[PDB]
Image (cartoon, coloured by chain):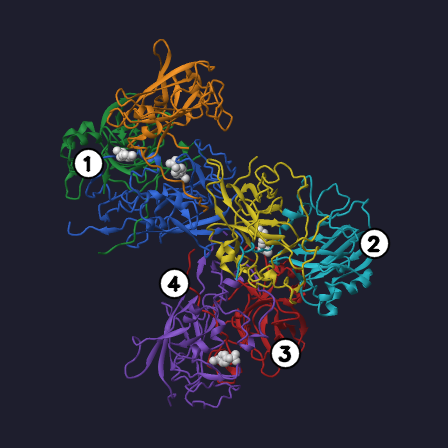
Chain colours: A blue, B yellow, C purple, D green, E cyan, F red, G orange
Amino acid sequence: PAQDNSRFVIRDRNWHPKALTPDYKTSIARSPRQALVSIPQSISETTGPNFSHLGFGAHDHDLLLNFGLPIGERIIVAGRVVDQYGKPVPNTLVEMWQANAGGRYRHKNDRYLAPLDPNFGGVGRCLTDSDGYYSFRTIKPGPYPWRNGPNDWRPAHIHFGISGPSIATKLITQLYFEGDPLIPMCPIVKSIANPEAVQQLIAKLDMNNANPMDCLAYRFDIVLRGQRKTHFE
Amino acid sequence: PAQDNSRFVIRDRNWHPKALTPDYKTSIARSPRQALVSIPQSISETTGPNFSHLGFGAHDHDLLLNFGLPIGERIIVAGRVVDQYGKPVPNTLVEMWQANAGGRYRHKNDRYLAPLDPNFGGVGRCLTDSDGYYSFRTIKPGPYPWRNGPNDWRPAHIHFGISGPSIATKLITQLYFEGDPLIPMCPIVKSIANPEAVQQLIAKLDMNNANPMDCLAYRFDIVLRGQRKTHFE
Amino acid sequence: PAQDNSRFVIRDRNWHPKALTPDYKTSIARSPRQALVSIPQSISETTGPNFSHLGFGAHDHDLLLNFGLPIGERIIVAGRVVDQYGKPVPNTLVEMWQANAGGRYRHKNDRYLAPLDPNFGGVGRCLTDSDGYYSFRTIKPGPYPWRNGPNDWRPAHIHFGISGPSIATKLITQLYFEGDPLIPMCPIVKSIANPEAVQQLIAKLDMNNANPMDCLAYRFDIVLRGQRKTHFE
Amino acid sequence: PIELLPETPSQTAGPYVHIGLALEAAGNPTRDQEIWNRLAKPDAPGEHILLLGQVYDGNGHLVRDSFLEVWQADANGEYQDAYNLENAFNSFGRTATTFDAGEWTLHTVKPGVVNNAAGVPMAPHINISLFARGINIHLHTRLYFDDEAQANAKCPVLNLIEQPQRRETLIAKRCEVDGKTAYRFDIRIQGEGETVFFDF
Amino acid sequence: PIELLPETPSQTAGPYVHIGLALEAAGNPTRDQEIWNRLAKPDAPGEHILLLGQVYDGNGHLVRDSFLEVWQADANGEYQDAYNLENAFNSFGRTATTFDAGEWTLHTVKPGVVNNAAGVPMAPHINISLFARGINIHLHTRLYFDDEAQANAKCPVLNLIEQPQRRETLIAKRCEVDGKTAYRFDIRIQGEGETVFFDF
Amino acid sequence: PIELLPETPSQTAGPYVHIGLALEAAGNPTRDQEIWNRLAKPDAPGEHILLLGQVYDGNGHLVRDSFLEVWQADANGEYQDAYNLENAFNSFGRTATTFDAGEWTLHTVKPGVVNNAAGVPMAPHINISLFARGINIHLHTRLYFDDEAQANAKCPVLNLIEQPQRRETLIAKRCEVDGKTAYRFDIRIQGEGETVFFDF
Amino acid sequence: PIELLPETPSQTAGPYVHIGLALEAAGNPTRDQEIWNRLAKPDAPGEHILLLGQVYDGNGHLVRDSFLEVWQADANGEYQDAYNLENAFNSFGRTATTFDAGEWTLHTVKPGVVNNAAGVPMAPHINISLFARGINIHLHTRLYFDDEAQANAKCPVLNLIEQPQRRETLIAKRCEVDGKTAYRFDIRIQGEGETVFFDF
Ligand SMILES: O=C(O)Cc1ccc(O)cc1
Ligand SMILES: O=C(O)Cc1ccc(O)cc1
Ligand SMILES: O=C(O)Cc1ccc(O)cc1
Ligand SMILES: O=C(O)Cc1ccc(O)cc1
Ligand SMILES: [Fe+3]
Ligand SMILES: [Fe+3]
Ligand SMILES: [Fe+3]
């Protein structure tokens, strides 16, 4: 069983998006009005599941084959998962989900007029390696309209969920593409007050990793709460 | 029949890409080694076809219907065609062609591994209106690899051909998308020495023209040789 | 035998000197006119010889003893060989050759009037260690005149040949010395378009490695093409 | 001051979180091994219980697109981190609310007591993280049991909530479903009886 | 000095120009009305002729992906600008080279004489624009006829080419195809016998 | 976009390359172990061959200061990477052009077939890199054998050269030297019959 | 991205709006022609109705300085854009809240049905814009009729409001005033029962 051997650096709630960000409409009614209650870290918060033993399929991380070939821009999305101390986070679970090349999601609730791709599901998972690296192969998603303001559009993005070493490190986020003109206009992106923080969600074109005459590649590195040993406790 | 009533401003061959631009390999053997011979304008050069009477189909300019719905980002591409004097060029022929959302063209010679879209052809045509405006509705094309350098990729683009009032104004070009990280790396884009000229080929996101919950829009204005009356000839 | 498990980052041919650099007269008739043909990497290109078993003599890397003592500025030339990812390249062959203190080469064809040095050959070889480090002990060479323009002088330099992990990495270059005023006047240096690329060829004075009361030291690190594993191939 | 690398900023999981983390729920085909709402196998030691609840927004409206993750000790108060489908018990699980009913369910055992860092025992609790469209960064909370008043009274964490009335929001009310032991734990994101959320 | 707005920069038509401007050639379905290589209807006045040619690169290799546009006066030396498929004659047309054979063909009549701006008559000619992958900006040229030496000798445009030997590159050589009057006009982009290209 | 550390820029080997890489040729004493032009020992399996050639500049003049490095599979189509003078076969060698005659020679064996990345076999070939004063960055080419036409016809690499005529520039002409099998491979850096050079 | 000229920013109408748009109410002499609260003349076709309501702030207090503008189709579901005092029906009107009672009144006819952009008919509605001190930019809402439930049920607009409960805030309660058909439409700017406001 797990043991309480580390402490995680406190989160910066001014770096992360606040709960109430009115331009993102739904957040009005879904943001707490009382202040969070801070609690000291215990074994309950400093431990979490390890997915080393989960039985992943052979194409869990390959969206081009996990669902004919899908239509759209073939790309590899890879990067490294490290903590705030720059330390790799090995054997950690990385899950992703996204729309198709037209911005249509394979979900009941998606009624957008862009069609579904008979050969595209849009779900992937990968366990990071010994060095904290992960990789996926998919197609680049299309922006999509949503009912917020009368003409709001989500910049193309890939959804990511990352476990890390504890429930204290778990995070869900969204990766955006270097240069998309839709990023600066998105109220969800704007839920993040610091422009520097936004930069952190932008995947960089990585020509070094592309497969000539096959697919392009984007690099997206992830930083989770720094992990340290307890001391003088 | 046509008459010799105007003169066109001389082209700036230092603004346009030169013939020999070695990084674009095929241009080595397809560029003339002798200098062009300048000739004074005559009725032969100052006149051209008028397509006012061509019988265009109802969806000639709509790539979403001119070929099920195609897969990919629905967009409108519109703009105005003016001359160097800022004058509109009405009733002029605008033709376009492009790949699918995956970067696959509907041509024999395209052997790229990205599949063809059963509902996408990629050819459009539109006659500009009385005010020089044109518009097309299509899906945004995907970048594609080509055999130049060992890892060259064309930034997503739409091919355009524009008639104008004379054969002196005819032009073929390529429209690129605002922010594409692939533009600065393309040897074809780079065939154009002036960075300012490149900017001219970049389509701007135009949220004003988009159809909420339907499609985005890009604005691409075209400038053809200025037209003036002869004088003291 | 060797196996095909690596891919090398595509060389940047705008970084390296172009083939045709007219100020460097000899390049005129010794540069292809047709474009290079790019081919996918195969075992043929991603493998190379390993010189680990080559039997190197005791003074192979010591030009002060491998040929009395040479006349000239006693120096140590050391550095590391890394790939573009910053990974060390251990057990790699590094070969060097240069003129003596007066810019005279110990070669038949060198009829420069500065005398040969009886205790100096001008050749060395070193296998990098586990950390990618190499070292040589020599005397600093002198610049020398050459029949290019009517008064062309090569800056002082040492020629280097590095094998790296494959024939795709093999490279030959020249090391120049920090602050030499001849540097910016050389047509061979100038074959390199980007001033930042030039900087990469300049060895820095390294007082840290110097042997007091004995010899100075210069630091020269080399970067071979980045090596990556194949993926989704 | 010393500054580390900044943590990657959170983003709402959005309305389609299910396609990524609750496949069945998305109404899409599942994979061989899925992380879901059954932490304990029939044969796992401890009192087997059923957890159910609803989530409410600030307008008192059901949130039908929530995604919850849970972490708890086993009946022995041990955290079983090595996730395996072969395990009789797994300390981690996932659930979500019905697009219809808007109710989540979880099948587990009652957690054993664990001590805080200072060596003081905390009352039995299940750590919960909630995600949904409209929530920029997930909300952390704890589920305690109404049938453990004695322990609840002495919990060092529960004791950190300033106002006693707020502590009540964290107590699941014991019930029975099909003569099976259940506990109902409703979460109120905002407004009246707003559920206590933590920062750690 | 006064500077106007800059003209949009040219870009190569690329290897797939056919899908956009030579549909049949692309091997794709055509539209109701297409602009192609038949300028004259059987019933159009003037000498009906067939034009054919090949295009060569600098290595002397056939260019099998070229696209050409043409503009010429009618038999009366009149430019018929109002393009219509109902026209017996259209002054404009389009052709392309076979991916196999690499030869283009055009069906027209021999153009009437037209005067330059100074009122001097130019020899009969067809204005041509060439496009292809590897050509950043299209090449302008003219096709003249070998059977009009007298006029050719006096053409004010032809007379602008410095070297007489270069003038020859612009003369189509009369032949006959199926006992039909034809003229062969080969274009050499680069090297030996490089075709004269204009700027206007 | 992501940018790595830039590769150290190449520089011409210069006229005196021999002093560093071809001691014998530089006419300087050699060391105990030198990497030279004998890839195979008389007892190495495979057909032993003699390879010779000349290198020409763009004026058709001999390049008497060229330096070449070769890389090839043994008879079994395997690359012997562990360089050792005791081996009966070494996949790596070096040669240079006579300051006099200006011809290089290599003593090896006809390489076995190896497959590309896609698993498609390539025709027997020898990888060559050429260095010399006037060459800012080395030239990469391959030598193919004239008596392997069937295979040459199917080579995935040779098949990448658009123009069929340029492929012939990579084919070594079989001959006999002292009743010993030889193949002559002439390299023309520029102009007429210019040898194809590769990038990878 | 393309940016147009920015729209002139809105500013509160302020407390004295009446002086400019509701002369009678401001208690100032009116001009010959004033745009007021009588949309229909007694002889206008359709069911004549009396509309009245109050406006409340977030404290539940009466807003006695509100100014309202209405836009509606006539009985035939047509918008009469040509404003004229002689018309028996005008699609446009204005009203304000009593400084005393604080109720506004309008005299019109039950609007006919009009379709949306998609051709889907909308339930009979009246477009309202509210202005007042404290309101930086005007509020847009629609008034629906309680006796049009079938239609209300199918309204493409009403159907856009996620929460069914909020739709009720747009339904005017039918009544009778002096045995004359009336409908009461109370607007709550904030808090409990807050009226839905639109953007378009
Ligand atoms: O919350 C929203 O409705 C906007 C949104 C939609 C999809 C998504 O994946 C993320 C946010
Ligand atoms: O000339 C080339 O091969 C590159 C290219 C490919 C397609 C295209 O549409 C434009 C240029
Ligand atoms: O190419 C040349 O002749 C100049 C040169 C001379 C010596 C040397 O080592 C390098 C280049
Ligand atoms: O809202 C207010 O009371 C301030 C105000 C007063 C007069 C005016 O005209 C506008 C605003
Ligand atoms: Fe999304
Ligand atoms: Fe293209
Ligand atoms: Fe030198």
| Cβ at disc 1 under 8 Å from ligand 1 | no
Amino acid type for the residue under numbered disc 1: Val
Query: Marks 2 and 3, how far apart in space?
Result: 50 Å
Dots 2, 3 in contact, CB < 8 A: no
Which quadrant holds residue G60?
Answer: top left
Nearest the eye: E7 or E184: E7
Give me the C-alpha separation between circle 3 and circle 1.
Answer: 91 Å
> Where's residue C29, x and y in %?
59, 75
Nearest to viewer (mark 2 / mark 4): 2
**Callout 1: 10 Å neighbours few (<14), some, many (20+)?**
some
Relative to the observer, which residue lies in front, A173 or F64? A173
Question: Disc 3 residue type?
Answer: His
Ligand 4 appears in which quadrant?
A: top left
Name, please, the residue furthest toward the top.
G179
Q: Disc 2 designates what residue?
A: E181
Q: Are marks 2 and 4 on the same chain?
A: no
Q: Which mark is residue D113?
A: 1
Q: Which mark is residue C86?
A: 4
Name the mark on residue F61: 3
